[PDB]
Image (tube, rainbow, N blue to C red; front, side, top):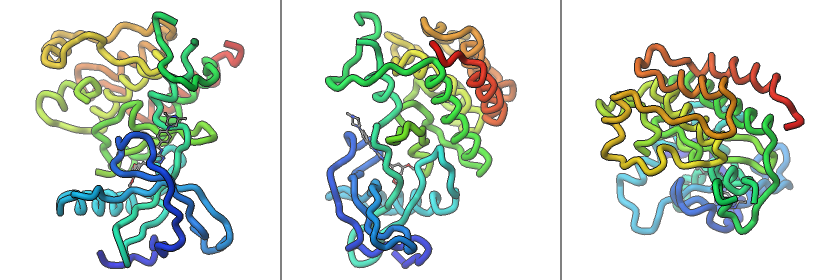
Length: 282
Ligand SMILES: COc1cc(CCc2cc(NC(=O)c3ccc(N4C[C@@H](C)N[C@@H](C)C4)cc3)[nH]n2)cc(OC)c1
């Protein structure tokens, strides 16, 4: 790997900590970076570090590098997982990125379900219920991250609550944008055609995940029937606790004709307005 002084951090500035989550983003560990900012060399910053597994292949290395390089080009946004640095010399490739201490959006929401036969809270460490405004805001932030990525001509291909991470301060950050059928637009599923419009379809499913507090889409519908049923016009019913307006947004995201779906730009404007009008008492 050739050096890139723009991003390089010396290996001994990282204090490698524990594995994060359960490997959904590869082998990622929590770490402390000493002097990640050259301006503040005596500060430690909690970061996430991605590296290769032990019995990796030449494919895995090229993918990690490709991921890193794409993230270098993508630029910063507060609602995406940002690249912070890399250790490419004198040892294994480390890709240093932002740390999101509250985990993926699905588990985040599930843990915040009311303590319920209908919608069961699987966490042994449940957390305070989210207000109705918090929930719309979570949708708005995801949309903002996607609006940014789409503006940089990035197609995600796997947008879903599990690929949004939540920081200590409850900021939503899109993950895994740098290199499942129940989140795919019919045209992606059928014909392998991935676009910003198919990401919008996925966003609709993600909205449904939000308003079911981490519910599993198309409950009990076998994968092998799903494209057939989507072709026939099957769409998820409204979550029990969802406004008609947010449901209509989901439905629009699931337009059969890709050109008729809203853009992320429009979704952001729409969610911005909905967030403003959502009661902060409920
Ligand atoms: C482009 O995209 C990425 C994303 C990443 C992942 C970076 C990352 C991962 C995390 N974080 C966790 O993975 C995490 C943290 C806490 C979790 N939980 C466990 C849960 C049971 N309780 C909860 C209270 C907390 C569960 C998961 N931050 N940054 C790496 C990357 O390389 C290049 C690129």
